[PDB]
Amino acid sequence: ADLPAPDDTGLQAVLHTALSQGAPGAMVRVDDNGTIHQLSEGVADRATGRAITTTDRFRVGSVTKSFSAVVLLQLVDEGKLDLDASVNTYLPGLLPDDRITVRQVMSHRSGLYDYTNDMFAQTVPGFESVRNKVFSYQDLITLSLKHGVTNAPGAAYSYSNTNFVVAGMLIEKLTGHSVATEYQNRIFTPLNLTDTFYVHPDTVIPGTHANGYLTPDEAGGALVDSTEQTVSWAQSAGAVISSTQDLDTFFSALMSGQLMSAAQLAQMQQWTTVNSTQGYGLGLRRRDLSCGISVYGHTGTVQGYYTYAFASKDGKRSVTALANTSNNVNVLNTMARTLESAFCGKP
Ligand SMILES: *C(=O)[C@@H](NC(=O)/C(=N\OC)c1csc(N)n1)[C@@H]1N=C(C(=O)O)C(=C)CS1
Image 1: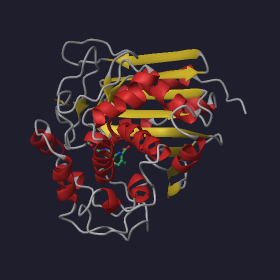
Image 2 (image 1 turned 180 degrees about the vertical axis):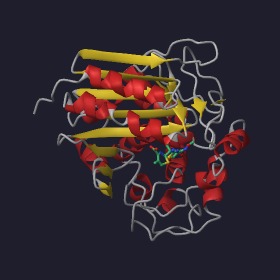
Image 3 (image 1 turned 60 degrees about the horizontal axis):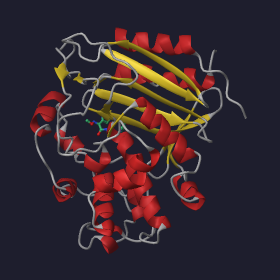
Image 4 (image 1 turned 135 degrees about the horizontal axis):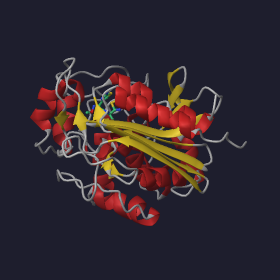
């Protein structure tokens, strides 16, 4: 049915709170079926003092998985990929088990160890070690394969970045084009997303952007500017750059059925249980809100940025919130509240 009115004061309180908890800046945009809501507080660059705004560009991290999933599902629509075929069928000798399918990799049921557990054990030293490095898809898979699988094929949900590194490799193999070209042609261009880029391995964010600040592991540590990095450790799992308006457009288009066939969208929303209030389909998350409504989209965490991009079942209302800091669980939990205010409204 019709959603309650978004609560702008509640949203203001959420942003203000994230600022009191360590986030230099924070903002949220709500596209409510043609009526826009925009709020922001804090700075985009804590050194120069520039204010953050809802037009600022940022790194979306893991939200990138929805972009990748959309490309793969279109490939299914075209007859080039079968979700239930072995990953080894399309990429011979890649994985140690032929029973792991494309569907399992897309929904995090493959058992592949997540190599970031090795890279970022120590947050700051980990970021300094990989920020300027360029990795191939093979490099990452091989890092994952040094460890055994964590469960039998399809047996259980376990989030792993590796799954979407494999996703990127699949896209390039089946199409013969880089993933950048694929995103541009199938998603960016058609949707006219002018603030959305996949520039890997470039370290600059084009145009006006919010800088990201990595919180150190030690309490009271000085913030580290993490804005410029290759994001080569994530690639098809988390290197997309976008804006609130573009992510709002992308998720509203996805949910209203404009990015693929109805048959594939239903496949994408085939939920594996994550916990009591969350689900994961094919590169898509479901969050159950307190007022009894569910939102669809994805979260993203990459050094210096926390992103929440969700939309209603029909795509009529979409929301993108962003705080420019990471490795701060208080800011992470607080920002999730923009969802309650935006979709559930005034308590
Ligand atoms: C997506 O963004 C990805 N995030 C990471 O790999 C993380 N660090 O990257 C520098 C990360 C995981 S949780 C955290 N505080 N940092 C995946 N996305 C999430 C998410 O928070 O949305 C995960 C829970 C799994 S890893």
